[PDB]
Image (cartoon, helix red, strand yellow):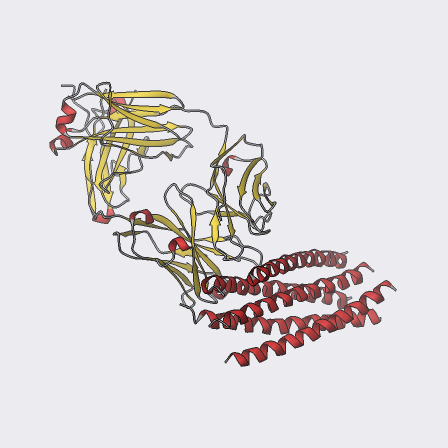
Length: 193
Length: 218
Length: 210
């Protein structure tokens, strides 16, 4: 009935939020590399490699999630639905994890640049959201494990629904984290030249 | 989506500020570059601005001589180039990248703005007839020593269209342009049909009518 | 960092055209391609490495081995005739660069020798104390041509200005050449000529003072 269709629908929404967030992240990454060049602030080469590596990965994940979304929608238009819905939660969780590493690298970038050019309020906010997301990601990992285990051998439906709440909270918290790093970049640029 | 201000004609040493209006999307989610193309030449990256951050970055070639700004409330990106010189004559495009999260290419381009840098001053053309001689004959009009482009040429108050061919202008080493326009006509019509080229050079408010008669056989 | 493309590529219509673009380290998803027709803005044809934007014909494809971006057009059509550029970013300092461009020619249109008309100076110009001979050159393909002037069998270097050819309306090319003289210079030679050389064969038009 409408329970599973409603879950596939919300997963479409969540993948859209992740695409949008990725777009903003891209902007922030670009802005930092640009400021890095102008400010001149080997340890940055390896950061640039991690940025690029995790950015490829996020692009893969987004793509694979798009493919899985389509199949899931086909399965509704037409067991394998449950399986795919659970696989679609693992894809979204992975994307959130890779985006979180990316965010953390951008935060690092901002800290390096601000130690060349208050921020204590900013720091406190960064840590609060970082700790929260770390904990939401961890709860999502445990629920994913539980849901995968059940799917091999309901409890399943409950944890599937609970996993939708987990992912949504993590994204909403990432949104806040993004706004803070945007704030940080704007605050740094406003001080050069 | 991206519409730029119009053609500019500039003296060497002066400045030009080229604008680019963006509509249809959210201004803060844009990435902008400026790209120039000299005539017959390649595309050249000048600089970037991410309006959300509002700081510009430049190719070193143009470092210190170009300023790139953005205005949120008008949705406009600007490019100012100072201490102009003749080799700066080019078409300038604003372009937009990060169309989507993984589009590093430039998805939208404005129409381009022509910037002409010359020490020449506005001058109306001298118009001379190119008389038909020795069954189709060619006759024309030479539009000589004018500045700037463009000139337009009609024939017989627009009534003559068939066989009209207006050639692109030569740029002379004096900094002035010259052009020619020819019509192919029935040879047997030269003593009967009168032919008049109508020349319009708007920049200097010049309208000239020139009658082109057959060369005499005497 | 430099992107290098071949100056020119030529394809039989229906065959596949390939345009390469070599660099140091084109990171994956950084290569984009642009179509540009005379008088027009560039148009994005491939981004990422193999992504076509909405409205781009399926016959366009791209690849990236890290050292070479390739644009491919299977079943090339007339309308595919244009200049193509590749673009990319520096990995560290995020500057943009373009390839030098590639002029892609679609074969099929026949060779056409130029139609040339030479006019002498008019009376009115001679009375205005100036003299210019006008050489009009039209209806040629391919669009490369060379122009030389002679005064009485002897070549004339000074006072020559010729335009670089432009695409007409049909798909042929036009160009014009101009020789500047004083009235005295003009009136003291038996004849002047415009020599237009196209694909190793030369058309000549001669003119002579009243």
